[PDB]
Image (spheres, coloured by chain):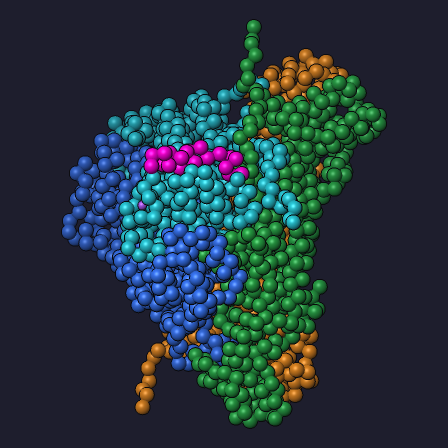
Chain colours: A blue, B orange, C cyan, D green
Amino acid sequence: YDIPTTENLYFQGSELSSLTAVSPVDGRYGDKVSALRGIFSEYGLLKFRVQVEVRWLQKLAAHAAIKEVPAFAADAIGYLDAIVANFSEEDAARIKTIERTTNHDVKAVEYFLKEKVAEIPELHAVSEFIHFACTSEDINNLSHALMLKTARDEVILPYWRQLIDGIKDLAVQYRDIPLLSRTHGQPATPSTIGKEMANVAYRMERQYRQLNQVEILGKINGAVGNYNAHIAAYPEVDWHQFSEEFVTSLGIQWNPYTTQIEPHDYIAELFDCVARFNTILIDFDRDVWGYIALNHFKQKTIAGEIGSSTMPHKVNPIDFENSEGNLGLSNAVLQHLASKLPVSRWQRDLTDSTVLRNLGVGIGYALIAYQSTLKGVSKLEVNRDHLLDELDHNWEVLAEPIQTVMRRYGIEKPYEKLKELTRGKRVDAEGMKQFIDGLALPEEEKARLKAMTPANYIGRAITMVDELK
Amino acid sequence: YDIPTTENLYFQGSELSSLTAVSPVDGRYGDKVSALRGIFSEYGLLKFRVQVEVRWLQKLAAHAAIKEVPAFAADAIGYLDAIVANFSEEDAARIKTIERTTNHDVKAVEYFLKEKVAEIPELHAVSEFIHFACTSEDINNLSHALMLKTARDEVILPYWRQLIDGIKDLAVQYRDIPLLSRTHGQPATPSTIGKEMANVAYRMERQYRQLNQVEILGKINGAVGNYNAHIAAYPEVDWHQFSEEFVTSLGIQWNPYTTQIEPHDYIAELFDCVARFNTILIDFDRDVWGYIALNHFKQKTIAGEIGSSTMPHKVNPIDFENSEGNLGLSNAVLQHLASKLPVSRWQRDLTDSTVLRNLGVGIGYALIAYQSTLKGVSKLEVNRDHLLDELDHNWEVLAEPIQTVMRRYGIEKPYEKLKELTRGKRVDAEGMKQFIDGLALPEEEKARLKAMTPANYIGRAITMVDELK
Amino acid sequence: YDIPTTENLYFQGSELSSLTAVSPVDGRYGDKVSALRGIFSEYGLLKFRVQVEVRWLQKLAAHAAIKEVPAFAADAIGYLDAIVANFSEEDAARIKTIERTTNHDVKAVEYFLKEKVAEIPELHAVSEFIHFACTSEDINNLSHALMLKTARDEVILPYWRQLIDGIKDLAVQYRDIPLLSRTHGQPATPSTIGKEMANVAYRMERQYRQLNQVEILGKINGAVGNYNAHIAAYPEVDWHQFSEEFVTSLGIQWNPYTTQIEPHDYIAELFDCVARFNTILIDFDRDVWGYIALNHFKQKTIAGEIGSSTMPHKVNPIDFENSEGNLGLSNAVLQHLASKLPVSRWQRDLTDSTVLRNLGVGIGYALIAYQSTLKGVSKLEVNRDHLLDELDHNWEVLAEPIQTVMRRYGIEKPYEKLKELTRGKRVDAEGMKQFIDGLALPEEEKARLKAMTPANYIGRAITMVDELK
Amino acid sequence: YDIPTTENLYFQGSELSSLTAVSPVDGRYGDKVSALRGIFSEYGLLKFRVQVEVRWLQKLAAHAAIKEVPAFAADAIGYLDAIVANFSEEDAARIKTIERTTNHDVKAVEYFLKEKVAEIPELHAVSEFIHFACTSEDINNLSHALMLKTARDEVILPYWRQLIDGIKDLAVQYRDIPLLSRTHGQPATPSTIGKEMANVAYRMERQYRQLNQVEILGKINGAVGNYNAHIAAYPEVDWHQFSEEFVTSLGIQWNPYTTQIEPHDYIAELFDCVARFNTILIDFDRDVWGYIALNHFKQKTIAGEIGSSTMPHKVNPIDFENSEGNLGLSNAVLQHLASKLPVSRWQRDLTDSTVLRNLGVGIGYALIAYQSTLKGVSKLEVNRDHLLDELDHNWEVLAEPIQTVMRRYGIEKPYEKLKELTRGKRVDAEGMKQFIDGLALPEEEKARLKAMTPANYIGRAITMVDELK
Ligand code: NA
Ligand code: NA
Ligand code: NA
Ligand code: NA
Ligand code: NA
Ligand code: NA
Ligand code: NA
Ligand code: NA
């Protein structure tokens, strides 16, 4: 005479919103990462598991040697396909309710699917072939592979393209604007703003190419990697071929040698590459913050906006700073996953399950940063007057070309002579010209050196920018 | 003739729930971290900023030399106090709406508060003293200090206490249960299960003590740390004393030397300590996973629960594994914050703002782990039959006490003789006894050695457990 | 009337030996890393800088448009080549002595080379073309590229090959030896020892391939990347072509877009890949330590060797443990370099110079680990008697194939029925057979299930091993 | 008829010098870390193990209940003490030679000591009491504790004191020199150079205090922590008291609850604190590099020194950059040790042995950085002319005090009015004065505001500096 009790209730209260979320990835920045909610959330994971389970059953049906699962009629195929396509938050809630009993999420998916097909006698007939011979990780690893492939193609690389193109566009806009370079933070041989942008774009494109080349791997092969259960029931089926077909049919590259888990090395490869690109963008964010500090760039201001609570005058590079901070966090999460995921005790331990729930987290921080950098870039206005005025107060940078021309034409101790003239000393255009005048150089060379200025001492910068891409 | 437009709309859709959250801290494990939503979320932060701003105004009112802010009547004090106490998600939404204009969160709080007091003429009268002389970071750093102090006292240390007490309780339960120790993974000198628990408890208590000792610091001193604006308006007020009073009135310890920001070293100290404790718990989780693998512990099973999707027999230490994975993630976030927060360019850069929104994240993962370890511990059942049977097959561990007794009584080359007998060799009780019998030892010593067994060769283990705490 | 003083003395005392070295990479393990001393030490770096500087001068000589550096006679070519080939520790000491004056290592190399060619009037004649138009980083980045290429081809990949081959050899040796698998540390579906080795080998080969594919990059282009000085002196020479020719002539891949430094992204790519391989080897070291703990492997013992200071019986997996610890350290250094090197302020800051002196350190720890794993592997002896005896006490692992066969043949609730029989329960061969006997299965299937044993329930393990490579 | 062979030769060649060392800690910077060679090298470790072993024997001799080790005569005490005091590299070489046989370093120390006392019949008589009841880790953990205590007191804290005092000295030198502050890299409320130094000094002193407070722990208690062997041989001796006495007699704090190893949590505490201090110094190095870039500081130049291979004019902050890079490396090593050392499998695994050989490495990098920062500081010369000229071009920073004074005196919308005047706009002294003139403020307040300048708008900066320490 057991009476109704509610230990199994799965209740989503009204407590969670972007205002009360602990993580800013779902809180303050929840709107910037909305693409990931369909991919890396518990809903997204459940949805991919359902897809993989349905596809597995469908392959068993279509395989001629598995006689106990007859080929499905159009009607049946459509009902299964709709389970996948129309998978809802209510469906997810059903699975969560079942898990309150099973304390096992994939077995809950299995029981959810057995409940789903109960009313269609043709599907109900093959109900015990749902999850046939599979281990939970057969379902999970393929789900994660599909999640990462989706994220890469639909979210990550499109943002990388916007950043590369945006920075390439700064290179073009500013191709011929001279810049007093800084090495060790000190005035050095001039470049152009555009050439400094070109360098970054070039670095980013290398990683873009590498991210596309990373293999996304998947496996399907039973409890510990050897098709034991498959062969026990169907010794005459070539499960090794079946596996390769199934994985590749999902658009995933096949990993034939595994334990219970797919080993996750490809995740470390994907994430090492995202992290390199993020590091390039940290470098860019910091450099631009620095060019803004030097007044080489001004930033556009927006009506109603407030720069500082106390200092009315402030216009700050806040978008680059937000980006820089989130890329740090992204990398910290990505590095942890990359280092930790590929170590699993013996034929596996379960530490990777909770950690893999965080795939979207590391990626989330990065997406938030990408959008911020993009915002900050749209506000940049180059300060040509400042750039040129600074160059015009740094005539000592012509010590290099003077000493190099002197070397060409056999003057004794050229470097040493210019060190004497300039190191720790203020020398202006007249000072540099008088020095050139006293040199034993051919007149045409003297004329060339007297015609140089810090602002035109830019070497091949403009042509480099023109040759990019 | 401007017409209504909606660029300023702050709309929270119905999109976010625990099912669709990107982070499992708000998703799968959202229910385990509900305490943090009132502390570290955007709502929690806004709520503390409001408290600090209201308290600042109240101190200006109560200070006799600030004549322009007259002392508040009971009525006024109560209205301000209710703003703080009854601060709502709708209030937070007002602040977010204002931020859509200001693009500055603390100035939005200021404008929100000016709107709030507009209808009370006594408060409206001193409206321009809201945020008086303050910089945003005066408000923020004190908010974060209050958040961390709350988390420490109300959330973190209570969980640490449950774990310490729980492990101390395993020490008591199992005080006298002999264990074949393992060093380098190999059979070694016996201990007891309880003594192995005692060691862990002792380590955890050291960190508990240290976390309580960490200073939680706060400052209030204007745009760059020097009270410039305060002194400009009120040169005769001792702002240095005012600062110390205000900070300490909030229950925070005073940091008198700062730039625009509080430097965050105390956050690194708090987090380094949480990380050490988490590392001790990783060690414990891994060791218990190992004792379960060896069958020294069985785990209780629950009706309806599923151990494996394919392997019906499985009972797995899933709670320890979940804990172990989340403690890794906790530490990775905590370490990043600890290393990054205390470096800020010149009088500050804004990278710390977005990073500090993640204080609850590192703490969230740890809380999820603490609860899991606690769950896994409640399921442990010691397997005395297995422990004793293993000891009874490892008589070679008596080589140590035999050789040490031989050393006491002047027998030549004792270690070397036992190495010869036992290293790489199987020796049972009869083999060990026959060896003892052939030794030139006093009879009472021979009798003592013949009476030892691996299971009683436990030294001072039981008394150590009894002396703990 | 200045008198002799000794501020410039460069004195190498007798203080440093492997016994007194602070780092164990030069101390305790100095003999394991002797290959790196010719590559990554200050001597090795100086030697490569000298090579690059000499090669630069030689290209200027051979270029028809640089008329001021006439083509070198055979005599001259040979004297320059010998400077490079016969570069000595005394030469390095000369450079260090010069640096005591210059406080600049590359300018010291330049002055060292000007001193070296002073006695050959043909070389002395073009003395001011040593380092012509170059910046220190033109010399350094190419040196580091040559160092990394040498390390990869001569040291790293050969060790990776020994490990891959060694582990593949364990796969072959042990192909058909059944193993009770462990998932979550618990008895699971059997595999073979050889198949577990095969998985690791397969993972390692993926990284081997990737390390070979990483680009090793170099640049040469003057103070800030734009050939400014080159064009100032020789505007009619195509320096962009000259650069590509020179870099590729050294066997390095060309990086055309740089600041003063080569940006170091390729170093992060090389090191991310070494780190993934090291992580795979940590996983292997830990698993083997675990198989040794379980007594699945015994280790061979050596005459005179001591297992423990106190416990005469001990034979420990010390080589795997040494490897595991050093791979941790390797990864920590490699990760730091990978994350830090590619961020450099504006056209560069000097933080990368001291950090790049540590390239050999991260690599050193890894080499020490590789040798240790190799040593530990040479000592492994499989314990077939233990492996088989364990399998024979774990008949519950046949619950999986029984339930899967039941699913094939339409028996109701197969998983649930086996969960009832086995979860948390001891069932032996007779218990499993009696259960099978009571099942409504075709006789041939019943006979197949009654003929299975944990030791033969190994699926496709043996054929997988045979198909590897 | 065995013939002489040389498998046991321990040969230190002539290969290793500072020029050929792989690590720059023994190579390029070998001279900066010479203090650590007596502490953390293999020689240093061997020397401390010898000390601990000799002290253990001496306590057994002096204990009245251990009748088999008679109290030592003065002669004997002196011979043992000299073994410790006069321990040589030849002695270390003897131990290494023995290890070629034992493959066990502590047993080699034991055999080395048995050989050492063989000629003194009184010591030879108690030869089998060398290492009595001890496990290797009893000897090792106490050695490491003594190494860390020595490093802390003799090396680390003295350098921290030099840095704190040096920075405090910059605070004094520059107390009243106004600085245009930068927040988000943008011109903000002025401070003084000295006050910016004071903040850093204050942070460093907090860590200095904390490093002194960290407990340095040690244990002595046999193979697995329970005195098993001690009690087997001497059941009537109170070993728990003996342990506490012995450890504290060495000047180490007692850790009574351990496995085979001391758990290393105190090492994580020491290293977390060094890392916080190093992070404060990274912040300082970066800020000073930035003040040098802005020309707020010039650096003194030295005769003969070279700033750049190509750019004769360069004077670079190379000492701060060297420091910054080495502090990164220090922290990476320290963090790895702190995270990894306290996790050891069951009653211990041997991964900590090789890792603990690196204690001096993390500390080495830090020492190299400390010396560099000290060098760079000795070269600083403040550029008052530049600092003041910059302030005089940044009159917009007076928007803050103007708006705050306006708030005091009830002017409508003060912040908003100053935002309108200054945000994104150039306003000079005349512009600011004309704005003040038009304000409805009391004349004395108008006069105060008209008398302010960016250079005197420094609030309480000077008094703060005066109050430091
Ligand atoms: Na079929
Ligand atoms: Na594994
Ligand atoms: Na008042
Ligand atoms: Na700072
Ligand atoms: Na030529
Ligand atoms: Na850069
Ligand atoms: Na005695
Ligand atoms: Na442990």
Q: Is residue D294 above or below residue A305?
A: above
Q: Residue at x 56, y 46 (%)?
A: C100
Observer-nearest residue: B89 or A281?
A281
Q: Residue at x 61, y 93 (%)?
A: D443
Q: Position of residue D26 (x, y in %)?
A: 57, 39
Q: Is residue B274 above or below residue A18?
A: above
Type of secondary structure dominating the magenta stretch? helix
Q: Which residues are magenta?
A: C73-93
* In the image: residue B64, left or right of residue A279: right
Q: Position of residue D447 (x, y in %)?
A: 61, 89
Q: Position of residue B28 (x, y in %)?
A: 42, 56
Q: Is residue D72 magenta?
A: no
* In the image: residue D4, left or right of residue A180: right
Observer-nearest residue: B211 or C52?
C52
Q: Position of residue C425 (x, y in %)?
A: 45, 35
Q: Is residue C75 magenta?
A: yes
Q: Quadrant of residue D142?
A: top right
Observer-nearest residue: C230 or D366?
C230
Residue A301 showing in the rendered view: yes
Q: Quadrant of residue C85?
A: top left
